Length: 32
Image 1 (cartoon, rainbow, N blue to C red):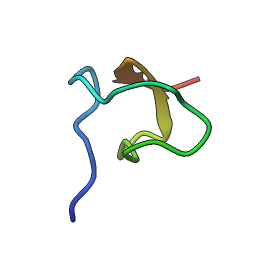
Image 2 (cartoon, rainbow, N blue to C red):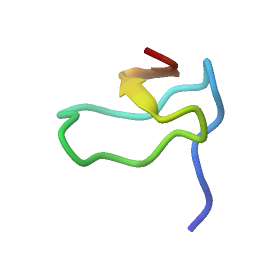
Image 3 (cartoon, one colour):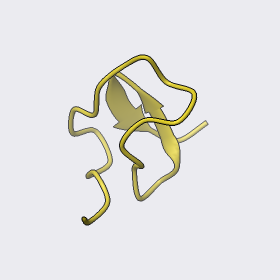
Image 4 (cartoon, rainbow, N blue to C red):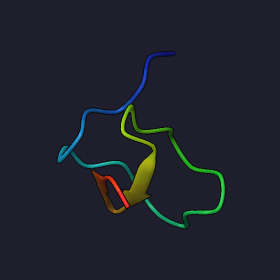
């Protein structure tokens, strides 16, 4: 387990998904 990197790829569907360190995931990790 780890976090996913900001502006690295996570996955979808995003409700719960692999968690980005900057929080937001929408295919790519971002911030919102």
